[PDB]
Length: 196
Length: 195
Image (tube, rainbow over the protein chains, first blue to last red):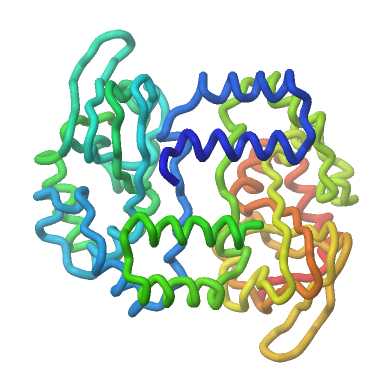
């Protein structure tokens, strides 16, 4: 709720505190945490608007204008489909050096860059540089099995990202299936990079 | 307390999207009115990607009341270490809902302390307290369990819980124990939320 990393860091620090865990264990834990941290593995899968009446949901949605949903990719989506997608889009800041996605891991969401620049790295080799407007994920998002990511994604500068968890994206797509048909078709056009 | 944490999430959401005070107000009111711990459980697994050695150290410092149940008499250390690492806790305020009738069970709950009401429609069926396990029976099936009653906090309460999802993942790796778990749960299950 600002940057995912700071929020996650603070959750860990409470966990460590509420169980009066020793300093050497807590250090090892925090050491391991930022050594293993990546946004993709820390994403916020909550959905706090889920239990609101549809009128309240519409009034809320009406006030949002998510950059992500402005892609050509969403030109064909119905008003209701877009309102639901807009209610489950989240954000996270990302600092230089920070990992969005570590190679080999499961893809958990699609990511959109508001601002910032980022590098794609298979092993040790830039394969792409992304920036404002770029889309990140896979081709086969409805499968719905698992998607091992073929490269790492790190922030070069300070980034602000938008995302939708895949679980959240598929529940919504199941609901607007004629549109889903065009998600799958038109995705290649905006998919700035494919991690399948 | 998930309620307060979740409330903060929501106020952040309001603040960041520069939402009108009137709409903000409707949002907050409908939050306390449709709130239930079950529908807002902590589902993050912060320790999931830690080395097995570091995970076994953290687990040794835990001693969850929830796992002391006779229901886990026969579980292995690997099973108990994992069970323990995914146990969450929430403190409840009086009148606060744990579950609402009709919603899908998301977790199983243990009562470290407090008195709770079980109320199907408008009748009290039980008042629960220290040591009561709230759940369902075919917790493994598994699809969706729509709960049969409401549960609300009466005094201040302190719950431990395990999400059905994380619990199904551990039981998959401990199949013999899974079998015994399913047999032995009826023994410790205080109230059954199935329909």
